[PDB]
Length: 302
Image 1 (tube, rainbow, N blue to C red):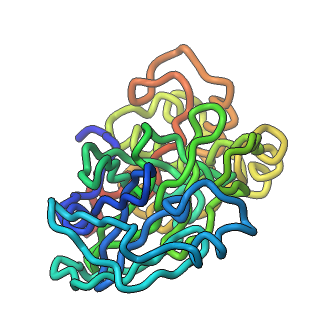
Image 2: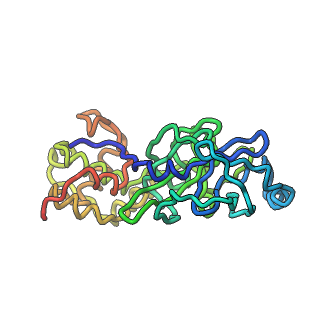
Image 3: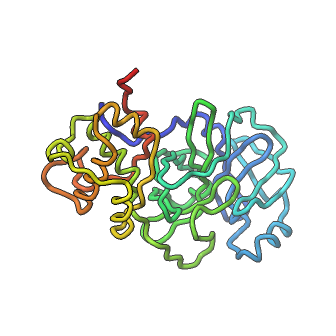
């Protein structure tokens, strides 16, 4: 029982995290096969036009890559979106079975927060609709990766680049594509605020029912809001449109509560409450993906 933010185990990632130093700039990289990926501003602080010229003017020996003290020699430079791809003279025997995947809105992933090429801590983040994360990042953490672990292997989805006003964090996938409408430049970037993720809130409400907190649903006569009706309300109250998830079939099977009851509860609880806590809170929590809740709950039919 109980509900916590679950971080994927880090052993596979720790064996790929490296330090990349080029000049005064210090940040982190990802060692896979015979190449290292790190943010492009390792070259320096430049503008879209300048990145190609900075890479051209660079020398392979100016990049110093360390994995647990051992030097990795660069044998090739390349730009991959907002990332630098440095071919190295040694193949990472610790390269896991992995895929580069794009995190989708509402997904959780784990941040391997690193400094000087050493993971110092892990936490879970949630991809918001505007492509930003509510992370915890200090100077030197650029190049920290976000990842998931499946039965098929490691899934690298994120590399950290920048901090935005209001303790908001942005980055790219491992193809160097930024997740939001921001850029890796020292410029004031005010980005649209993120609506609350309705799908995730449904998962959190189910997790409450799984843990004997059903006052919001059982306490009232069965109250229901259709998906169509809810989507219209959410559009004008700062909530995302409901998106279904396979986990809801499992959750309603174990709890007897339908999605439509949860949507009605969301409308009822949208402004917060004070009757009783729900998983220790008095406001809806949108930070738990359905996958995160499902790995903390049991199926009951089979």
